[PDB]
Length: 137
Length: 137
Length: 137
Image (tube, rainbow over all chains, first blue to last red; front, side, top):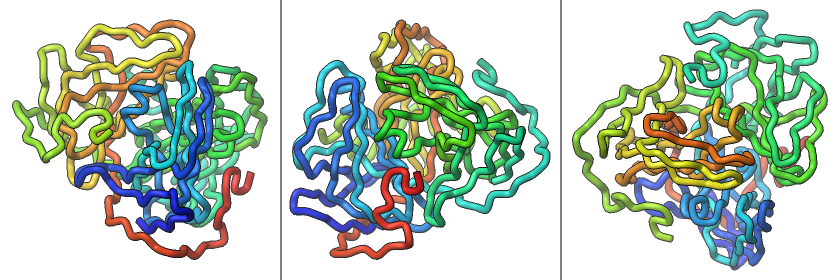
């Protein structure tokens, strides 16, 4: 995970334990996420990631449970070289305060497949088929 | 990524750049996502995916930032052979308009492990344990 | 996927089909997710997962479409040995009822990369660069 810090308030990502899935992402700014609203939180970070992954901006559990916070968007492509902004949603009834250095998300390097697309004129099945939504219930 | 188009308004998925994580998913219909509400957007697409993955219906960043849009649900199994419908959530205060051909999500082929389940009568730890929510804070 | 059941109302995870991406997670308790609100649903489960993954608490499609339900948080680390609680968000206008044995989420073992962090003083590009949000539109 290659990381270039873009200002002096940016914080280098790091996983909080050796079995942690994600790298902590901190705000490099003072801002607020409005109640029942969204805001983009600047991190001051540029990143370059390994082949065969994308970086997912994932939620921190404590902020979800305690402040009704989620990340929105969050699909950071391998070819993305701009500043990472964390899109926060606040579903709660009161503003969420963000200050410099505060951890606001966690970056997970999801392994993915990016094969060619093949258009076909029919597809077979398994047993499960158009097995929709509540396929079993 | 094998794709069968189910009507003439469906659009073949394609990644927008060579380092893109996801394949663009377009609506094959005119519909609306109500304010503070949800709608399923038909894509007119059937898919078959590679072994060891699932297809995640992921959000587009622009729609999240600019229209408070998210995907809901979005776990498309390997054995799913029905029409892919994109579940959109609109957390904003005004309807989100969708028209035919509009890109509404992106499909990411997430690599996953699907081993057998093993029930045990105890589990050891690391240092981190029942380290809950804000494990460090 | 190693699983220790913590009480007699807990349910062993299992995938609902052989091509299913996720292992079903059931509530071990009677509770409610308030309208436009959140609740943590206890599962009575401890888990240990394979190397190179994390367990994602993912939404069930039927609950999203039919009850406007999502999972929040949901990043369960490899070193997590506490009881898995499922964070549910209810964006709908009415309480969501949960009873013992009810399936409330699905656990997906996402493959991820967890390399060292490398801080750099510049990053090159592709064509796509600071290609932001709606990079193409």
